[PDB]
Image (spheres, coloured by chain):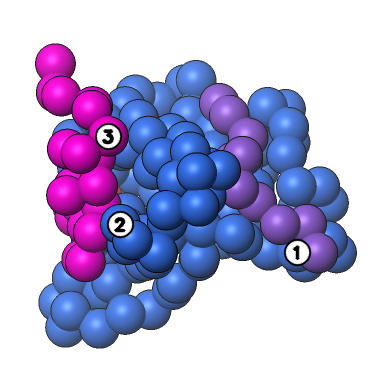
């Protein structure tokens, strides 16, 4: 039960923002910007690939992702290097994996270039999904009041 | 599951 007041959220997402330990399941190209079914089908496909590679002794890449006013950033855990950066305005839909409480994904990109990024969180995925919800709503609210710049 | 209110389809 975390405090989700505006002032708290602002401090939470400013700068580097919130960091979470996880593993990259994969990135899939999808035909639309949103859709529960669209994301679940994509998640199932990406996991299918992961399972096939695991049978061959492969493992998912260890990463840490951050949620900040800069959107979602994925860093390689071993080196700390930024590998993927999806700005808030490029993220169109967030979806939890109804078959896995430790996985979620998001659709990013403009029209004609939608991609579903699938993540396997170290801990439960819920707090991450909720941070994204709070981040987006906060940015919407600040922009409406025209105070985004004064807070980011 | 939710849509991002500040997404720009452009
Ligand atoms: O026990 P097994 O059969 O070897 O299989 C592992 C098990 O499913 C772990 O939970 C999983 O880590 P996550 O839960 O964090 O995905 C790991 O993935 P990895 O190989 O990609 O680390 C699998 O290899």
Residue at image point 68% right, 63% down = A109
Q: Is residue A77 visible?
A: yes
Residue A89 as seen in the image, left or right of residue A24: right
* SS of the residue under disc 1: loop
Q: Viewer-proximal residue, A92 or A114?
A: A92
**Residue placed under numbered mark 3 in the picture:** A6
Kindly indicate whether the residues beneath marks 2 and 1 are on one polypeptide chain.
yes
The colour with which the image depicts chain A is blue
Residue A16 as seen in the image, left or right of residue A133: left
Compare marks 2 and 3 and give the one earlier in the sequence: 3
**Residue placed under numbered mark 2 in the picture:** A151
The question of residue A135 being in magenta is answered with no
Compare marks 2 and 1 and give the one earlier in the sequence: 1
Q: How crowded is the residue under tag 2: few (<14 C-alpha within 10 Å), some, or many (20+)? A: few
Residue at image point 50% right, 66% down = A86
Q: Position of residue A129 (x, y in %)?
A: 38, 34
């Amino acid at each position: 039960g975390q405090d989700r007041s505006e002032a708290t959220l602002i401090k939470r997402f400013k700068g580097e923002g919130v960091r979470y330990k996880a593993k990259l399941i994969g990135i899939d190209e999808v035909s639309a910007a949103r859709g529960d079914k669209l994301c679940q089908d994509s998640m199932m496909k990406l996991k299918g690939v992961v399972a096939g590679a695991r049978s061959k002794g492969e493992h998912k890449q260890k990463i840490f992702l951050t949620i900040s006013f800069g959107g979602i950033k994925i860093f390689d855990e071993k080196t700390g290097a930024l590998q993927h950066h999806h700005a808030v305005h490029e993220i169109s839909y967030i979806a939890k994996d109804i078959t896995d409480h430790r996985a979620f994904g998001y659709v990013c990109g403009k029209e004609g270039n939608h991609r579903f990024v699938a993540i396997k969180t170290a801990q439960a995925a819920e707090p991450v999904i909720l941070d994204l919800r709070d981040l987006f709503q906060l940015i919407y609210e600040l922009k409406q009041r025209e105070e985004l710049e004064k807070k980011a | 599951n939710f849509d991002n209110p500040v997404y720009r389809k452009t």
